[PDB]
Amino acid sequence: VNITIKQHTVTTTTKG
């Protein structure tokens, strides 16, 4: 899975 990862990455990436 790369959904949760990409998600948890939005926390440190704040991608919109």
Image (cartoon, rainbow, N blue to C red):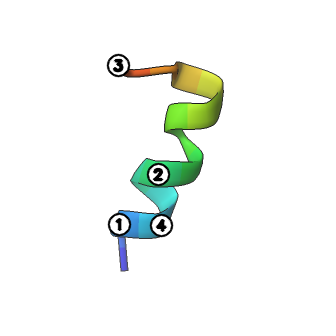
Tell me what residue is drawn at x 50 percent, y 59 percent: 5
Tell me if residue 15 comes above or below residue 3 in the rendering.
above
Q: Is tag 1's residue or tag 3's residue first in the polypeptide sequence? A: 1
Q: Amino acid at mark 3?
A: Gly
Q: Nearer the viewer, mark 4 or mark 3?
A: 3
- Badge 3: few (under 14), some or many (20 or more) residues near its Cα, within 10 Å? few
Which residue does the numbered mark 3 point to in the structure image? 16
| Helix, strand or loop at mark 2 | helix
Mark positioned earlier in the residue sequence (4 or 3): 4
Q: Secondary structure at mark 3?
A: loop
Please report the residue visible at 53 percent of the width from the left and 22 percent of the height from the top: 13
Dot 3 and dot 2 residues touching (CB under 8 Å) = no
Residues marked 4 and 2 touching at CB (< 8 Å): yes
Instruction: Check disc 1 and report the residue beneath it.
Output: 3
Q: Is residue 12 above or below residue 2?
A: above
Label 2 close to label 1 by CB (< 8 Å):
yes
Q: Residue at x 37, y 80 (%)?
A: 1
Q: From the viewer's perspective, is 9 left or right of 15? A: right
The image's mark for residue 7 is: 2
Inter-mark Cα distance, 2 to 1: 6 Å
Residue at which label 4 appears: 4
Q: Are marks 1 and 4 in contact (CB under 8 Å)?
A: yes
Out of 5 and 16, give the one closest to the viewer.
Answer: 16
Left or right relative to 14: residue 1 = left
Distance of mark 4 from mark 2, alpha carbons?
Answer: 5 Å
- Check disc 2: other Cα within 10 Å, few if <14, some if 14-19, many if 20+: few
Q: Residue furthest right?
A: 12
Secondary structure found at label 1? helix
Q: Residue at x 62, y 33 (%)?
A: 11
- Depth check: give the residue in front, 16 or 13: 16
Quarter of the picture holding the C terminus: top left
